[PDB]
Amino acid sequence: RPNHTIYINNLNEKIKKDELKKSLHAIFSRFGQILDILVSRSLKMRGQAFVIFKEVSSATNALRSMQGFPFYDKPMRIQYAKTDSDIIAK
RNA sequence: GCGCGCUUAAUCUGAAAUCAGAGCGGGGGACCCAUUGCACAGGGGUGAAUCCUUUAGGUAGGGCGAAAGCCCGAAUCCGUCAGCUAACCUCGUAAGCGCGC
Ligand SMILES: Nc1ncnc2c1ncn2[C@@H]1O[C@@H]2COP(=O)(O)O[C@H]3[C@@H](O)[C@H](n4cnc5c(N)ncnc54)O[C@@H]3COP(=O)(O)O[C@H]2[C@H]1O
Ligand SMILES: Nc1ncnc2c1ncn2[C@@H]1O[C@@H]2COP(=O)(O)O[C@H]3[C@@H](O)[C@H](n4cnc5c(N)ncnc54)O[C@@H]3COP(=O)(O)O[C@H]2[C@H]1O
Ligand SMILES: [Mg+2]
Ligand SMILES: [Mg+2]
Ligand SMILES: [Mg+2]
Ligand SMILES: [Mg+2]
Ligand SMILES: [Mg+2]
Image (cartoon, rainbow, N blue to C red):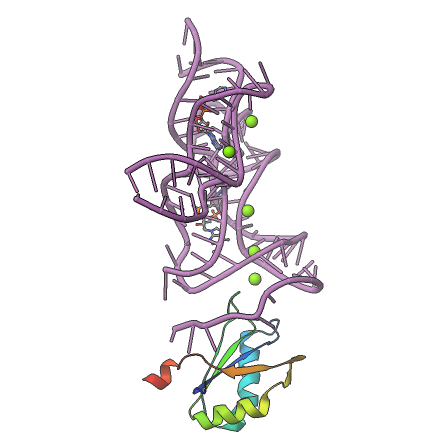
């Protein structure tokens, strides 16, 4: 179900948070203004990221356009976040 | 208090003691392997002490014992955090009882 925030998984877990967040911003900022990027390397949350766009249209185009993209030698897997981000609800 | 036996990683050596060694342990922590995970109590550690039913029984598991059998099946701590893991870093060495003089 379409959301302001997109959920990406199947990401290379060896890549550190700063570099990962930097690369994600680099790649997704062209689709529109990005509100934020949440990345965690914990055991449960590693290999995943949440990209929160200012506009939902950006999220949709980004998902449709970047689906399966070779990123750090692994094809990105992109779906929509199950729940709205704190930033949008507020 | 002391003698030797018990659980335990809980012992031994410095006149006594975490203040220090040795011994014996716990945790953190790469390559490789494993993990596909919906974020903003949870997760995890030591330990045999985990689990289902109406305060209780049973139970995975565990202790003593030559085997019969008798028991235990607690407590607690890190604080949103930890897989395996070599190097390297860090900590613990409390306590409760059974026999006899
Ligand atoms: N690690 C463990 N895992 C699971 N259960 C455990 C356990 N450690 C102990 N238990 C159980 O709980 C009781 C605790 O006894 P405790 O050691 O306080 O007191 C014990 C012990 O201090 C002493 N004792 C037992 N066996 C001994 C022996 N062979 N020699 C000298 N003393 C002994 O007499 C008491 C008799 O205890 P008993 O064996 O009937 O009962 C024990 C035991 O059955
Ligand atoms: N991987 C992990 N994930 C999440 N939390 C973790 C963890 N590892 C340890 N912890 C937590 O932090 C404390 C670790 O203390 P420490 O580093 O001194 O590591 C140990 C050790 O110094 C000592 N210890 C415990 N069991 C031991 C054993 N069997 N042998 C030797 N030392 C032991 O006491 C501490 C453990 O008990 P404490 O009550 O201090 O509680 C633990 C526990 O609550
Ligand atoms: Mg262990
Ligand atoms: Mg049994
Ligand atoms: Mg024994
Ligand atoms: Mg570890
Ligand atoms: Mg790790």
